[PDB]
Length: 267
Ligand SMILES: [Mg+2]
Image (tube, rainbow, N blue to C red):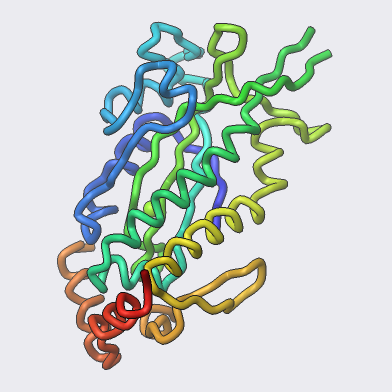
C-alpha cells in the first residue's frame, strides 16, 4: 500500500529518514536518489544528509534557492512522503527469514511505482493560474523496517521534494485545491492504484522466486500462504529484534524449508 503525508520540517525530517534506529533490523537504509529531476541536478546513488536537508529547505546544489525566510521561519513547504509498505509475509521473510532478494524485489517494485508518480509532476504557472505537466521530480528513497506497533514492516519512504524544473527554472510543485489539478491532488486520487501498482510489481517478482501468494484483502492485498503473519499482528533496536526472532521461533514455522520449497519450485 502507499501512504501519503506532508513532510514536517527540513531538519527533523533529515533526522527521521536517516535515523539508524529506523533501519536497525535491515542494517541498511539503502537510500538513493531518484527522479528525472535528480539526474538533472547530478544527484545519484547514496543520499548525503546535508544535501537532502538543504533540498527540503528549497536550496538546490544547482544554486537555485526557493526558501522564503519570514522571521526565522522558512515558508517553503519541504515536500511529500509517499510510503510504500510491503505485505507482512514478505517483511518477515526478508528481515527475519534471510531471503534478501525480497528486499531487492521491494525496491524494484517501489522504483517502478515512483516512475508513474513522477509523470504527474506539475507546476502552477498563472498566465488565472493553471497546472502544466512537468514530468520530473527530485526524490530520496529510504528503507525502514518497523511499523508504528513495533512489528516487522519493510517500507520505503519516497520523499518528494517540493521542487520541479519548468522551462529551465526550478519551481514548487502544483497545488490546486478547487479543481484538484495539482500534483498532490492527482496523487491522492490515484493512491489506491499506485499502491496497487507497487503490490502487483512486487508480486510478479516474488512469484518468479518460486513463492506463492494469496489474496487476503481488497484491491489485491496479498500474503505468502503459510507464513505466521498472526504472530506479528495484534526503545532498544537490539532488544526489539531479539523479540521478533523469539516470537517467530515459537510459531514453529520452519523458514528455511519454506525457502527451499520456493527454490525447488522456481526457475
Ligand atoms: Mg518509518
